[PDB]
Length: 5
Length: 222
Ligand SMILES: [Cl-]
Ligand SMILES: [Cl-]
Image (cartoon, rainbow over the protein chains, first blue to last red):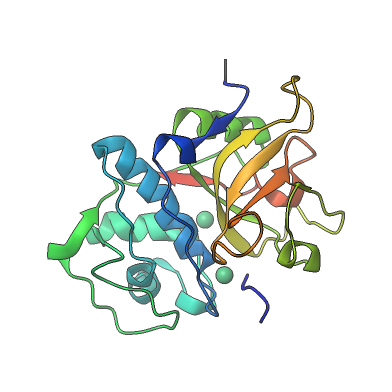
């Protein structure tokens, strides 16, 4: 998962 | 007879926290973290490894770069390739690029990998105690995880089966005097040191495989 921007 | 707590960061096995930015490459950071600890255990030298080398070059083994991948397929790539470059020589740019692996810059090798018994937190605890940092998958698909700040993370919406994020278990612990009180896994993330607790998170331990931490764990054999 990616960090939310 | 395993220790009541473990922390490989305190023995020199773990590099500073990295940041995958906007690329689906958490699997590559979990895999370099595990190989970094095994190479340190083997040579006494801590060398940051290249996630971009894995993103760009391990599609033959089944990984998909910034679209996703698996730590076991990364350790399979390192074995078949004969090496992995340092972070310094093959820098991270958070996008899929042409494979530029250079053998002369390789600083790590593996002979294969070990799978921890699926679903078994006691097998994971034994691997963490006896081997070093261990690559694991988890369900990080929650606002509570994005804004985690401190303490033992426990999220009821967590799945133990449908996982979406690769991280590194660098230890385990408890609070107070009783080793069974408030147990947790010490987990290194790859969202920068600014996320969470200096880049780490404590996940509830021995609470029915919370968030899937022991569902798909592995480590490279060096
Ligand atoms: Cl990812
Ligand atoms: Cl995997």
